[PDB]
Length: 169
Ligand SMILES: Nc1ncnc2c1ncn2[C@@H]1O[C@H](COP(=O)(O)OP(=O)(O)OC[C@H]2O[C@@H](O)[C@H](O)[C@@H]2O)[C@@H](O)[C@H]1O
Image (cartoon, protein in one colour):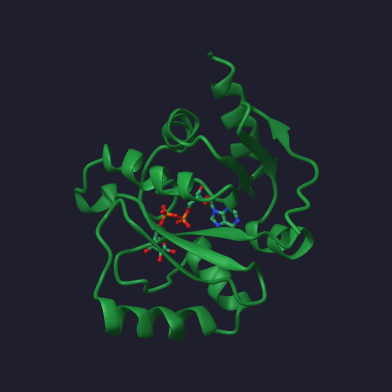
């Protein structure tokens, strides 16, 4: 469980590896995988789609059940659903969607949810479909999260860019 290998240490609690998050979840057996979600837990085309695919759509049903009972999340919030065959738990976290005019400051609120979990495997919130700059998302991650976060960046060119950007310390 939580057997992370091959990561680059960026800070005492932020680690980064060039890897697909769904394949890492399977090799590492993490307690908490982070989904980059929207407030209706409708799992579209990024990390959320891939996690859902790997659970054979179980995440989507469970999500709708959760949404039916509880209603939609706030931007910058989270919920703890099941991780199914990927992890013990899946932390659904809703970053701001800047393509839809939401406030980038809420990215800090989004990453604060990580601090309720000792250890997580996560992607870079809001950095794909939601339109935030990956480098910014990484900066907020570094400055906000205090627990152990292992970041999976599947694009080798973005990994290289991200690391180079972090060295402007
Ligand atoms: N399989 C993957 N593994 C690792 N990183 C990934 C993967 N797919 C995408 N990424 C990276 O994770 C970051 C977040 O991308 P998204 O998943 O699109 O996250 P976000 O921008 O928060 O989009 C939220 C929206 O996407 C929908 O899937 C979701 O339902 C919500 O509507 C980006 O750097 C993206 O390149």
